[PDB]
């Protein structure tokens, strides 16, 4: 029942600072060291440092000395990491991870930090319907184009028992992200039964639907 | 710093096979107190890492006994017996005996399965996108194995290289296949100058290219 | 450097 809930993702400008949190539940916060770990996209894990919530003692990887500051608030059972002088190299997922004799027995879900001058931009959502058949299934899609920062979530109103979904990782294109999602449904159900993709982009707080039309 | 070197970088394994991952440290991981703080983690696609093994050979609560850790000093091994499709991901070794604590570079476990031909679908630009001045042509290549696949675009039979972006999914733990999108982005006026759009895939499962096309004149 | 997790104090 141990849970580590980290704060939400953040887009921040180069040169600025950011402070993220790690909220512990299901155990006595002071009983166990809290570690922090960095993972750059597609790269290995790196140990940043550790704090003893009992007394605030800290120990840092010297690679992050002067980059990361670890603190706790005992009353709120919360650990914090503050990063300063941000550069593109600081864009990463950051995890808190709790000691249990073993070093990282429980992990938070991570906080995604994006360091960039680009502004938050909601996506354009475009329906992907087949061109101008006799088959028993049909694949449809939605193209989610021109958004920033990551991420988006695409859902479909298709029958779960009779459809299959694929989510393709986003790529950067002219400073903005583009992704797509496909759904396959029985051809007997389309176009008679409406198929709609719902696209959520939390950073812009948008939730847009696109109906698939022949 | 203590360097942790993992081999292999990629490990393909069949269901029920045994996988063996090696971790070597640049210096002994035996602490002065006699303990060896060598641990193994698994990071599944899209998830946080999870502890598997601590102090070389001890399984964390809930980790089944087909995961076994062995070794000593500077050389360690993780063996995953009776591999299951859900074992895919990146395995990391880790040492906490010396500050700074350091991780190995990872070993990506891939599930081997029977060849599976891609289901290919091609889509014209939406009218909505065209009004905006852009034109993306999208091909989906779904549920195929092995992962290696090459996509060629043609416009009216001529090879089109510029403007193509390809994105693979990670391996699917349910059926061990891959899927990928290939997207050709043009301007509206460029798109409307031509008739046929073709995505062509070279894959182990076909002696010939796997072709999918639409023609703007078939409406 | 001092191993805080093992030593408990540094």
Image (tube, coloured by chain):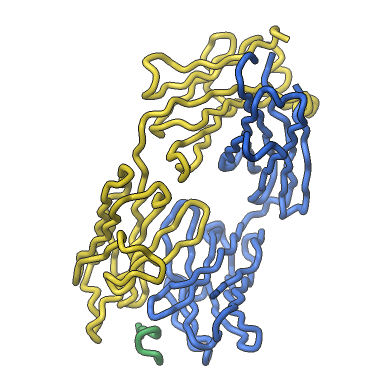
Chain colours: A blue, B yellow, C green
Q: Is residue B117 left or right of residue A19?
A: left
* Identity of the residue drawn at 58% across and 83% down: A72
Q: Is residue B103 visible?
A: no
Give residue B51's position: percent from left, percent from top: 41, 67
* Identity of the residue drawn at 38% across and 76% down: A102
Rendered position, A175 above or below A126: below
Give residue A79's position: percent from left, percent from top: 58, 79
Q: Say which quadrant the N terminus of chain B sits in.
A: bottom left
Q: Is residue A23 left or right of residue B37?
A: right
Give residue B11's position: percent from left, percent from top: 31, 46
Rendered position, B73 above or below B164: below
Q: Quadrant of residue B30?
A: bottom left
Give residue B131's position: percent from left, percent from top: 80, 25
Q: Please tell me how many numbered marks the rendered image carries.
A: 0
Q: Is residue A211 left or right of residue A83?
A: right
Q: Quadrant of residue B90?
A: bottom left
In the image shown, does B193 or B171 lie closer to the viewer? B171
Q: Is residue B66 visible?
A: yes
* Identity of the residue drawn at 72% across and 55% down: A203
């Amino acid at each position: 029942e141990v849970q580590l809930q980290q704060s939400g993702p953040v887009l921040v400008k180069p040169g600025a600072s950011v402070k993220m949190s790690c909220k512990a539940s299901g155990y006595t916060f002071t009983d166990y060291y809290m570690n922090w770990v960095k993972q750059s996209h597609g790269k290995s894990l790196e140990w940043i440092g550790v704090i003893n919530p009992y007394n605030g003692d800290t120990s840092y990887n010297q690679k992050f000395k002067g980059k990361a500051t670890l603190t706790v608030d005992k009353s709120s059972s919360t650990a914090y990491m503050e990063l300063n002088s941000l550069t593109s190299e600081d864009s990463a997922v950051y995890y808190c991870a709790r000691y249990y004799g073993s070093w990282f027995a429980y992990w938070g879900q991570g906080t995604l930090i994006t360091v960039s001058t680009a502004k938050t931009t909601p996506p354009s959502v475009y329906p992907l319907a087949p061109g101008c058949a006799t088959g028993s299934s049909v694949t449809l899609g939605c193209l989610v184009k021109g958004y920033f920062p990551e991420s988006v979530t695409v859902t479909w109103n298709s029958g779960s028992l009779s459809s299959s979904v694929h989510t393709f990782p986003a790529l950067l294109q002219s400073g903005l992200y583009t992704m797509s999602s496909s759904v396959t449904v029985p051809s007997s159900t389309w176009p008679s039964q409406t198929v709609t993709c719902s696209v959520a982009h939390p950073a812009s707080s948008t939730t847009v639907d696109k109906k698939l039309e022949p | 710093d203590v360097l942790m070197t993992q081999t292999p970088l990629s490990l393909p394994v069949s269901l029920g096979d045994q996988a063996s991952i090696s971790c070597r440290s640049s210096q002994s991981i035996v602490h002065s107190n006699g303990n060896t703080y060598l641990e193994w983690y698994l990071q599944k696609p899209g998830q946080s890492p999870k502890l598997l093994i601590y102090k070389v050979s001890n399984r964390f609560s809930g980790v089944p006994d087909r995961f076994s850790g062995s070794g000593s000093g500077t050389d360690f091994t993780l063996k995953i017996s009776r591999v299951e499709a859900e074992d895919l991901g990146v395995y990391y070794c880790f040492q906490g005996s010396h500050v700074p604590y350091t991780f190995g570079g990872g070993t990506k476990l891939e599930i081997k399965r029977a060849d599976a031909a891609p289901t290919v679908s091609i889509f014209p630009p939406s009218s909505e996108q065209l009004t905006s001045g852009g034109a993306s042509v999208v091909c989906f290549l779904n549920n195929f194995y092995p992962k290696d696949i090459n996509v060629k675009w043609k416009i009216d039979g001529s090879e089109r290289q510029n403007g193509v972006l390809n994105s693979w999914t990670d391996q699917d733990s349910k059926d061990s296949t891959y899927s990928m999108s290939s997207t050709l982005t043009l301007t509206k006026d460029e798109y409307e100058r031509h008739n046929s759009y073709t995505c062509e895939a070279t894959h182990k499962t076909s002696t010939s290219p796997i072709v999918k096309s639409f023609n703007r004149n078939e409406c | 450097a001092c191993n805080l997790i093992v030593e408990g104090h540094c």
